Image: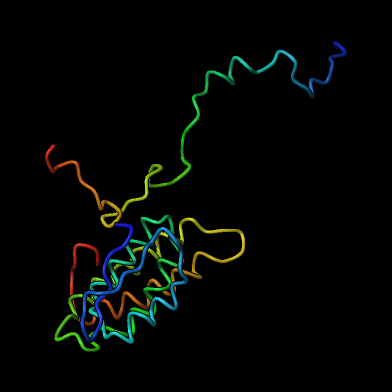
Amino acid sequence: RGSIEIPLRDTDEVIELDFDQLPEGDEVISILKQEHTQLHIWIALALEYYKQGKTEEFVKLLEAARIDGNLDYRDHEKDQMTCLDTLAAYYVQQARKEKNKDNKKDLITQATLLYTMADKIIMYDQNHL
Amino acid sequence: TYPFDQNRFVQYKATSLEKQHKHDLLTEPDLGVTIDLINPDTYRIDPN
């Protein structure tokens, strides 16, 4: 919403990040991953950043969420394919709002390569095609 | 022969042939909409 929950390792369900302020997304990766937090929260705060009106830090913090597919998660690789299809769609979406400086391929390369790892685990998603 | 003016210029103008043309809208080739199944976080299909 404006503050959803980030679970801890010990005495979980205690800490919050209020989204009315804008923290940097890289320290978010940290404060999530010292807590071995489930991959679902990475999608949830990505959606929080997107509903906060962000398309680029939103799409680059999830690149740091591409590392932790099944880190301590007990088969949340379904959650990693959901993570990676978001970049496979929003790299190619942010390539359409291209600017004067980069190329379209400057995002299409990352979209196409990450899609290949997206199809390593799962085939013919409703977003793969 | 007649000494015709070289008609290198438009003053009639061609505006009858011009504003009769209705102009296409091709700003975005998929017709001005971002095509996405992820940004519908909301849905009106719920009540109501």
